[PDB]
Image 1 (tube, chains in turn green, yellow):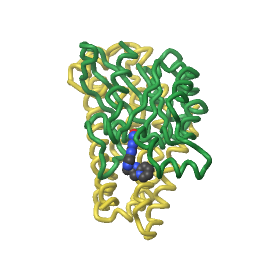
Image 2 (cartoon, protein in one colour):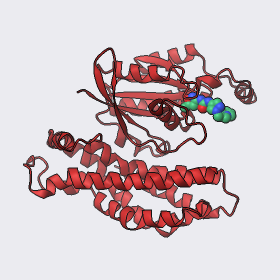
Image 3 (cartoon, chains in turn cyan, purple):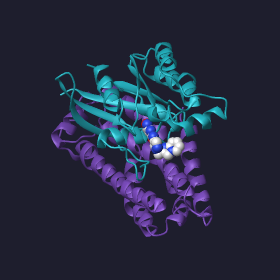
Image 4 (cartoon, chains in turn cyan, green):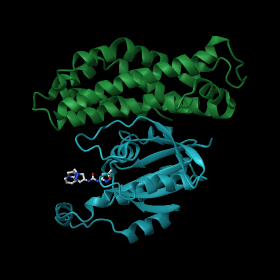
Length: 177
Length: 179
Ligand SMILES: Cc1cc(NC(=O)Nc2cnn(Cc3cn4ccccc4n3)c2)no1
């Protein structure tokens, strides 16, 4: 039965660990956000065909440019992530994540994922951004970034509300089948 | 409360890391050193390259580090000192990281499905590759847990600063040692 290795990359501000925990437990962790998500596998069925989905976190490796690629070989699909309310994380898709993923894994599918969808319409978040002369990342910006990096899909989700969350991992599997 | 959640996670994930390395050594490694199964000429007597110094890393965590972390369970604000005390032991992650590419190519180019057969036979969710990335994950994770304790410990909290310093230095030294 088809085994799938999916690596999750992107800035600390994406909330990679929170994304993966909220997906696998079907719940925002809420009380306390764990820092540790250990390599995970589960059977999910997608378009009928059952599948063994493997999820690796990379939180903690954001500053270790030579250690990060130790996770990259034999990946089936990458999630390249940015936070919809961090413009720096979005630019880093282009400056940092795409270059090294493409360098190590030329022919591996990328899903572009915008996280923290629930914060894009949050007054306090919006104002905190306005005070730095920034706005949240909007849908067309992610579409444009997706095209620029060859991403097979651009998808937006909240770990908090679960909006679009299950779709991210469905589409990661469909990018492989 | 938050410093207690972080300490609990530190300990629970330390226990899991020890169980993980133990499983890797007593399945994937034991099958190579055992003499119970036929070893691809590609990898014969190259367990040194495949597993690097993971035995020595496991011995540190299993003999020393988990027992000493446990003694700091009720002293989360002091746990940075645990990392200062044992700083020299963490140097073996430099050796481990340096070797890991050679490990991965050897398994790719020369192992065929030896380890996949072992995985299936033992019924393991994790591949040899999943197990062998774990030391790289663990050694970059301690600094995240110490940063979390810093957001919620008084300033009787240079017993975190120095610990974090060490646990930033080790992964940077390991990073800087790669080709
Ligand atoms: C990976 C991921 C997370 C996510 N959405 C969230 O985490 N959303 C969210 C909303 N409330 N909280 C707690 C909290 C308090 N806060 C104050 C200011 C700004 C942010 C903030 N978060 C969390 N979507 O994807």
